[PDB]
Image 1 (cartoon, chains in turn orange, yellow):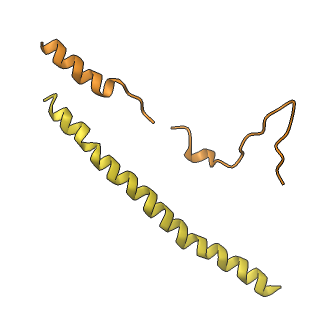
Image 2 (image 1 turned 120 degrees about the vertical axis):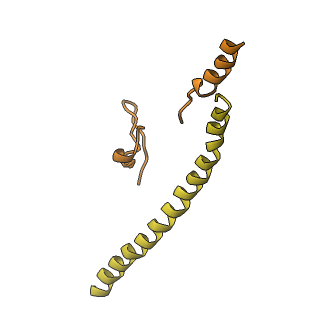
Length: 42
Length: 48
């Protein structure tokens, strides 16, 4: 019976297998490097 | 009461075969996706 109400705190969803989390990517450079390479080549 | 304990034990065993199933499906979709991302690397052949 979860009624996750606290005016002083917020409860964490404490069911996350911490061992298999916090490693997505973004890596803009994954492709920008290629764009820029071509540009340098240009 | 023993049957209840059996029942719970076996239910946990049933989960195992089904964890194997979930991981089989979850891992597999990612495997396909990052086979698809090999073309990021073929598009790195492009760098070549």
